[PDB]
Image: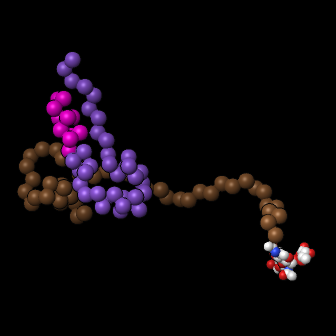
Chain colours: A brown, B purple
């Protein structure tokens, strides 16, 4: 996880990397906030 | 016909989405879809 060169070294399971382009991992945007949207009702259920 | 569309399908995003527990369970199956990703990438290169 140091840098892309080390990541592609780990992906190839070798310390020397030949010339070329290698697929290593996937980029994904992590979420920032949590959103909850429930109906505005507040009457307690007749469970009791 | 000469070539077909180059499609790359990812394991962890398809089988498990963005679920860490599902990925941890998927690790038990070994390297099945390291093989799958490799095969799809090889087809992609063969098209060019
Ligand atoms: C079963 O019933 C009990 C008792 O309730 C009372 O007696 C019954 C015979 C009926 O006449 C009821 O209408 C009557 O209220 C329930 O206990 C009560 O539950 C309510 C709801 O949570 C409690 O209210 C809260 O209590 C405290 C202050 O005391 C604060 O959190 C709130 O301001 C709110 O008032 C009430 O205190 C409580 N009463 C007693 C005697 O403990 C019980 O919940 C119910 N069973 C089930 C499954 O709901």
Q: Which residues are magenta?
A: B37-48
Relative to B3, A47 lies left or right:
right
Instruction: Please check the rendered image and state whether residue A19 is part of the magenta-colored stretch, yes or no.
Output: no
Q: Is residue A19 left or right of residue B15?
A: left
* Residue A44 shows in this picture: no
Q: Position of residue B15 (x, y in %)?
A: 38, 49
Q: Quadrant of the C terminus of chain A?
A: bottom right
Q: Is residue B39 magenta?
A: yes
Count of numbered badges drawn on the protein? 0
What is the chief secondary structure element of the magenta stretch?
helix
Picture layout, residue A45 above or below residue B17: below
> Looking at the image, which residue sits at the far front?
B29
Residue farthest along the top direction in this orientation: B1
On the image, the x and y values in percent for residue B34 come to: 23, 50
Name the foreground residue: B10 vs A15. B10
- Residue B31 vertical position relative to residue B14 in the rendered view, above or below: below
Q: Which of the 4 image quadrants contains residue B27?
A: bottom left
**Quarter of the image with the N terminus of chain A in it:** bottom left
- Residue at (32, 46) in percent of width and height: B10
User: Which residue corresponds to the image point at 66% horizontal and 54% vertical from the top-left?
Assistant: A37
Q: Quadrant of ligand 1?
A: bottom right
Q: Which residue appears at 78% of the width and 57% of the height?
A: A41
Rendered image quadrant of residue B48: top left
Q: Is residue A8 visible?
A: yes
Q: Residue B8 at what x, y percent from top left?
A: 29, 39
**Where, by quadrant of the figure, is residue A36 drawn?**
bottom right
Q: Position of residue B42 (x, y in %)?
A: 18, 38
């Amino acid at each position: 996880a140091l840098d892309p060169l080390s990541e592609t070294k780990c992906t190839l399971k070798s310390f020397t990397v030949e010339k070329g382009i290698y697929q290593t991992s996937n980029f994904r945007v992590q979420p920032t906030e949590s959103i909850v949207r429930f109906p505005n009702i507040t009457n307690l259920c007749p469970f009791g | 016909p000469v070539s077909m569309t180059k499609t790359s399908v990812d394991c962890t995003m398809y089988i498990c989405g963005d679920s860490t527990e599902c990925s941890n369970l998927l690790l038990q199956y070994g390297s099945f879809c390291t093989q799958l990703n490799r095969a799809l990438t090889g087809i992609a290169v063969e098209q060019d």
